[PDB]
Length: 145
Length: 144
Image (cartoon, rainbow over all chains, first blue to last red; front, side, top):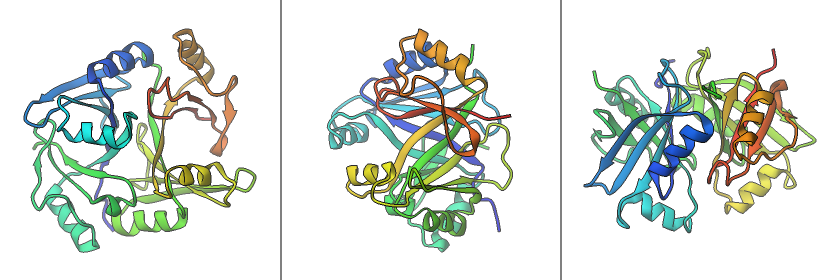
């Protein structure tokens, strides 16, 4: 036995306008914007929303993603769904991406990257192949230190 | 003020709930907390958690599978070309009646006029895709 995952870190939601999604969540749902990052090189803008002003240990957030250009992954995804905004993927928080990644590989799970890369913030991330997720794109994410 | 406690669970629809759960346990080390089977709705549901014990705001994964071809889960699957995947997100609330009122008062469209009964004895309702702007968002209150 061994718990590889701390909790669901966030559920990613793709849409055409990230700042609009945030205002809506805040004003209509009473959720809070905890982080907003714009990745020029990636052509994507991402905002983290939470049902509370302060995160609790295992509080899952909602990550809103939006395109900055037609070449971004989100844009291509939106195109694949003919402009239909929706759930994109799930991210599961891990204590040690390397250790866990090694474990998953043994289990027969295949990862998108051989080595973790920098995600939103100082987080090291990787993804499982869709099939490994049984139809769901599942991201692995570890917070710094 | 805050209308939502936390994301209660993320629903995942698939052909076989049992196979999915075994996979989650064997490969991911996740834990199966409860299993439910509703023969009238023709649906089997299984609640999974990344830990054996749920912490107060710990979100679970709800695995959904059909008992027959006439179930909404089967239709959703056919609608999606047989591809299993994320079905919806559910947000937990302290008082479903109080929150539903606030939501409507703010122009949100709810599927049911009055909270419905779901699995586990939970009162629930949903927001129209336009309300959840793309994703199906469920509202759920625990019975205590």
